[PDB]
Image (cartoon, rainbow, N blue to C red):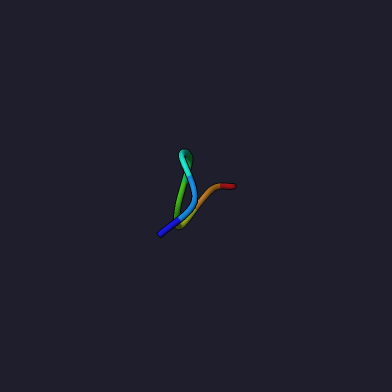
Length: 8
């Protein structure tokens, strides 16, 4: 889970 997901 990258900061932004789904909009990473």
